[PDB]
Length: 215
Ligand SMILES: CSc1nc(N)nc(-c2ccccc2Cl)n1
Image 1 (tube, rainbow, N blue to C red):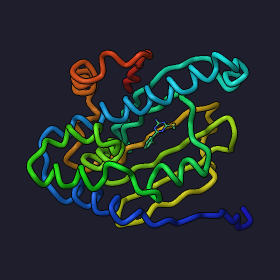
Image 2: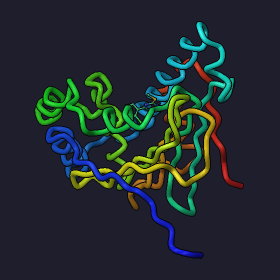
Image 3: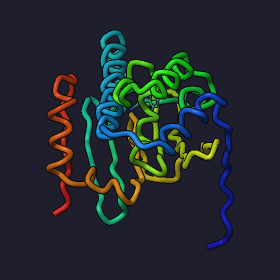
């Protein structure tokens, strides 16, 4: 094929977010399983946003009426994908919300964690997404909002992330978080383990979850 050209935007994480990511990555924490509760909570919040906004404007569901979460472990590529049909993010929302803008709870959470707080407290500080780095060496976030095109965000930490127009499979609306798991964290690809953690932490979320198991 003749050479194709793709635009990439590389961003630096806000200094404190980068400090938090390094703390989560480079330090042992027990109870890493809470990463799933945090991502399912973000999906649930996104599904509430489109649900309430569609009450006033039902055409916001032209990109899909079904409001749900799918969990997709892939043992071949060692990824766990969390997909929702929530509100999604515009490119601007994605750049702002996933690393460039200082988050209110970052400083406070780092002090709490170092003082011996369990990693489980992360969600209360509004930085729960970053718990993905307890189990993943790389995270890819694919998102589609009614007001913009589909975008792919990705980071292996190291203080930067990239954003590009997604060349992958289009989604009607919502967000897909792809966790590229660390070699020692493959238990999160096991259906019994995923079911255990969803029953323990994610029972009252408001939307149906479906776990897709590879035969
Ligand atoms: C606003 S739509 C949305 N959907 C999901 N699943 N997650 C998020 C989110 C919120 C904060 C930080 C990172 C993400 Cl990916 N945002």
